[PDB]
Every structure is written in structure tokens, then in C-alpha cells.
Image (cartoon, rainbow, N blue to C red; front, side, top):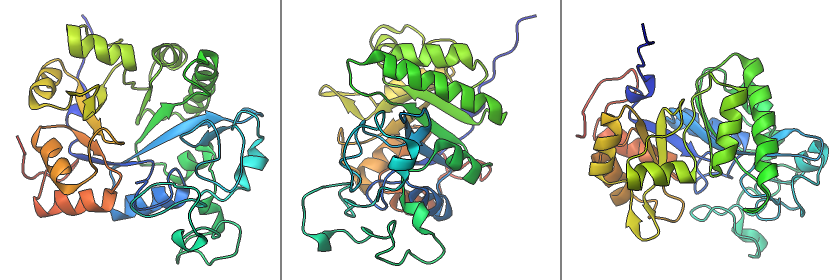
Length: 306
């Protein structure tokens, strides 16, 4: 008798999954941002992973530390100890993620990490550094996490494969499966899924394109399609596409990141289009929206926006 396939992520809605913690309300990919977001109501974290010269997975978006810290160089060239001393709020400006090159007054949390400014109450300086993935897992034992495998450059496929291999090894020892793992690079997803078959995954680019354009279903193990609002001038997070994805048994998670505005009108439209989660840059704002409309949430029934 074939294993009945029932996808639990289809009842995990609606999800507020803080994008990198919420890169417009807090310094991205820091424990501070993550802890802040969950207290303000985030159901799930979205984070990015790279590996250091000594093969530690760290939580950072870009391949270089230059945009988000007071340092310079690539993550792959730095040991975890060199990465962890940097100020990961160095360039943070509310409403604008990380923008280097402004007057020092622009940056309300620059210097908390290195001891020049006092941390917000109840946090420590280390909350404003680049964290080990292992420390994020240890800090969030009962919180789901969406983990995106990053690389060194679009052309450096092995660095994706290297990171996918490390990620599976570390995730497998936790015993947890309340993750969704994905990558823009399709091979890395297949490599992760080979080494850790029990962790839920979402497809990469060619997998999304194949399903969105041709109807070809994604790789075995996919529990959700994780999509931008728009890609190459075409609208992706439409009600039609999400209704078809639910009919095929996948949940849908929508992110913004410049393909559409992070604002109340856009959040409300994507909620209206039946998506199972949004990845806001403004997690407190999305939480205010979900509450006042009384939208249904995991373990809290309510309004269905469909």
C-alpha cells in the first residue's frame, strides 16, 4: 500500500516568516532581529547560509561581509572567529536594510556589537554579530526555520554544493524536520535532499520555472513553492497560480525583496491571493495587518481570506 502523502504545510497558514529577521526593522540575519521578530509575532524565520574558511555555517546573505558589517572580504576566506568579531549592524538604516557610505548618525545600532553603544534592553552585544547557524538552531528549538543555501557567485556552483553538504550534516544531527531548505541553485537542493531525505525542501529556479511555465511538478520532497511577487516583468503570486499549486498539494510562500513594495497594500493583496505565508521585510507591520483583519494562523482559527 503506497504511503499516503499528506502535506502538513498546507495547514500552517497564514505564516509571518520574518525575512532575514525583517531587514527594514532590524539588522538582517542577526540573533537580535530573529528574537525581536518572534516576540512581535513571527511564526517562522527565514535566513540565509554561507560557510567560513573553517567550514562553519554562518547566517549571512551576501558572499562578502562588506555590505552589512565594518569589515571586508569574502565569508569563505574568513575563519568563524574573524567573522564573529564584526559589527553586523554597522550599516543598518531602518526602512532601507544596509546602506554603506552615510554619515555616522544614520545608523542607530552601529556600535552595539563592539561595545560603543548600549544594547536595547534584554539583549547582548553578541546578538548584533554574524551568528553561527548552530547558535540560531540552539536559540530557536521550537520555531520553524526556512534556510536558503547561498553561494560565492552565480558561476561558482561547487560553493553551493559545499554549503548544501555542510547544511545536511548539521541539520541531520538535530533530529528536527520543522525546516524548509531551498536554494536558488537547483543542484544544491538535489544534493541536500540526497544527504538529508527527511528535511522538507522547496525547489530552485529551474524547478520553479518548469512548474510555473510547463506544469512539471517539482522534485520529490517539495512541500512548498517559494516565489517572488514578480519575476522578469511577469506576476507570479497570482491567485490562479496559488490555487493550482494548492490543488497539486504544495503550499506557497511569497517574498518581496525589490520585486514588489514591502508595504500594506502589497501585503494585503498577497494575503488575499491565498498564499500560506509572506516573508515581510516589516514583520511587525505584517503582524499588525494579520491581527486587525483577524486572519487565521497556525493553531488559531479565524478568517480565511479566500
